[PDB]
Image: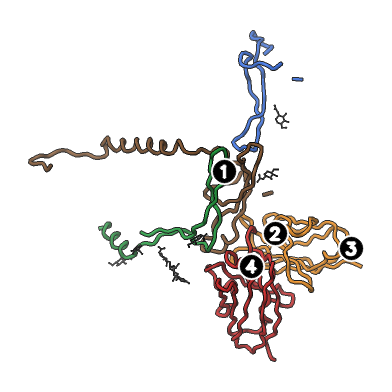
Chain colours: A red, B brown, C blue, D green, E orange
Amino acid sequence: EVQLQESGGDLVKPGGSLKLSCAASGFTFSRYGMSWVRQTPDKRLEWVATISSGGSYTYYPDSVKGRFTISRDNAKNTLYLQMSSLKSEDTAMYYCARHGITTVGVAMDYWGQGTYSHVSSA
Amino acid sequence: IHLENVTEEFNMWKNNMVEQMHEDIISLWDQSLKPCVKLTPLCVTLQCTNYAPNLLSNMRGELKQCSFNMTTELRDKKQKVYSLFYRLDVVQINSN
Amino acid sequence: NLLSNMRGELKQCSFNMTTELRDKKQKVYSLFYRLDVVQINSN
Amino acid sequence: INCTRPNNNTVKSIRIGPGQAFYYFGDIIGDIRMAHCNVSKATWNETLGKVVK
Amino acid sequence: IVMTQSPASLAVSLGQRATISCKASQSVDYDGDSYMNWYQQKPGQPPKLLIYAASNLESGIPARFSGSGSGTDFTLNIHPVEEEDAATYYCQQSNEDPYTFGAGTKLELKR
Ligand SMILES: *[C@@H]1O[C@H](CO)[C@@H](O[C@@H]2O[C@H](CO)[C@@H](O[C@@H]3O[C@H](CO)[C@@H](O)[C@H](O)[C@@H]3O)[C@H](O)[C@H]2NC(C)=O)[C@H](O)[C@H]1NC(C)=O
Ligand SMILES: *[C@@H]1O[C@H](CO)[C@@H](O)[C@H](O)[C@H]1NC(C)=O
Ligand SMILES: *[C@@H]1O[C@H](CO)[C@@H](O)[C@H](O)[C@H]1NC(C)=O
Ligand SMILES: *[C@@H]1O[C@H](CO)[C@@H](O)[C@H](O)[C@H]1NC(C)=O
Ligand SMILES: *[C@@H]1O[C@H](CO)[C@@H](O)[C@H](O)[C@H]1NC(C)=O
Ligand SMILES: *[C@@H]1O[C@H](CO)[C@@H](O)[C@H](O)[C@H]1NC(C)=O
């Protein structure tokens, strides 16, 4: 119900010393799961999922290997990630979303905010 | 009492007291189970699908977020419930 | 029944009966002698 | 042997009626790890080598 | 790895019917068929659910469309259309190890 405040100023040549943080909402922060979807021009845009409380994933897809580093904080009810050593063919990280229950496979039942930040050659 | 200067033949597998341990535990088990609560009316038809972070675990198996109708306190009232059951407790019949 | 020495009573009969599941009924077909059936006072 | 069950998975109870307090499974809170058992490795090697002799 | 399907960027003459399909990104799916749902977005909005749990209409949207599903190969359908219906519809189904979609629509009413 409450959207997710985001923050992105990703304008850095390829060294990925680039922190990006999520927010909280009015719903409970535990007992659910989150994911991350970026934005490319018209090519289906990202598949990076995350875990529940202490879940058994750190990278969801391939081709992000050694660069993903998702974390989660139950205390201040807000997670963040770090995308080190950034490659080209890469715009930015854009969206946050929630898994939810009473679905079957997985679904992104809410959408916080998309943030655009082109990274290369300022 | 220890015995002295005595031998004896011995044979297991024909002892009678193994069956007397077998028979009374059967009679003990049901007698402890009988006078408590019965339930006939539970096994009613039901539609069912899996739970969501079942796919997010080492246990990618079966949890079956599930629901049905059950008779209430009063005979002319029904109610809706929501519960969980493992795959080894449920089977389908051969639309949801 | 009308084609025998026993021209009496067989009563090829049918009703509704509950199944193993409580929300399903089923149709049957069976036989009962008139010494085991009696009517109430249409078929 | 040590054997555990991780998810402590709180319960609920309704009434069939009259006087049949039925208990049923509630809801998961937390992660999900399936049940398992640990066992000491080298001792299990040792007794299996012991029994085969 | 998948191989998704869509015919093209579509169009409609406001004639109540628009069926777009994605037959087989991969192999078949098991008894808990687990094919996830279709999302929508327009350039003035973030993405948004249409359908939930592979079969049935979402609590939150009105009751005016649905979709078919059978094993692997299926499609959508629609039922009388209007202004805010012409949008971009994406087709993600597969839920085992990766999450994927390659399909997509560009639908617009015909003048
Ligand atoms: C049976 O064997 C398993 C296999 O190692 C044992 O599991 C281990 O349990 C410990 C205790 O929870 C886990 O460590 C924990 O890691 C978290 C990470 O944040 C930390 O916060 C905790 O303070 C703790 O250090 C360990 O990861 C885990 N290893 C696994 C699952 O591979 C288990 O303890 C053994 N015994 C029983 C009775 O199950
Ligand atoms: C429960 O009963 C109601 C009564 O009409 C029915 O609409 C509903 O589909 C039933 N649900 C189940 C799971 O049997
Ligand atoms: C059995 O139940 C059905 C349900 O409507 C009814 O139509 C039929 O007449 C019943 N038959 C008998 C023998 O009661
Ligand atoms: C599991 O145990 C913890 C121990 O403090 C308890 O607080 C909690 O209510 C239990 N149930 C859950 C997480 O469903
Ligand atoms: C099982 O748990 C007991 C608890 O005190 C511990 O002493 C023992 O070492 C454990 N056995 C293992 C880990 O094999
Ligand atoms: C068990 O220990 C012996 C040494 O005593 C070693 O040769 C053997 O490979 C071990 N087997 C297993 C299954 O650990």
Q: Position of residue A37 (x, y in %)?
A: 66, 73
Write down the quadrant of residue A117 in the picture: bottom right
Q: Position of residue D11 (x, y in %)?
A: 53, 52
- The residue that label 4 is drawn on is E99
Instruction: Name which residue type carries label 1.
Output: Arg
> What residue occupies the far left of the structure in this picture?
B5
Instruction: Name which residue type carries label 3.
Output: Ser
Q: For mark 1, give the secondary structure.
A: strand
Write down the quadrant of residue C9 in the picture: top right
Q: Is residue E56 left or right of residue B55?
A: right
- Using the image as rendered, state which of residue D3 and residue A62 is in the foreground: D3
Both marks 2 and 3 on one chain: yes
Few, some or many residues within 10 Å of mark 2 (<14, 14–19, 20+): many
Is residue B94 something one can see in this rendering?
A: no
> How far is the residue under mark 1 from the one under mark 2?
32 Å
Q: Position of residue E55 (x, y in %)?
A: 70, 55
Q: For mark 4, give the secondary structure.
A: loop
Eye-nearest disc, 3 or 1: 1
Q: Upstream in the sequence, badge 2 or badge 4? A: 2
- The residue that label 2 is drawn on is E52
Instruction: Name which residue type carries label 2.
Output: Tyr
Image point (75%, 56%), residue name = E67
Label 4 close to label 1 by CB (< 8 Å): no
Label 3 close to label 4 by CB (< 8 Å): no
Both marks 1 and 2 on one chain: no
Write down the quadrant of residue E60 in the picture: bottom right
- Using the image as rendered, state which of residue A11 and residue E3 is in the foreground: A11
Q: Chain of mark 2?
A: E
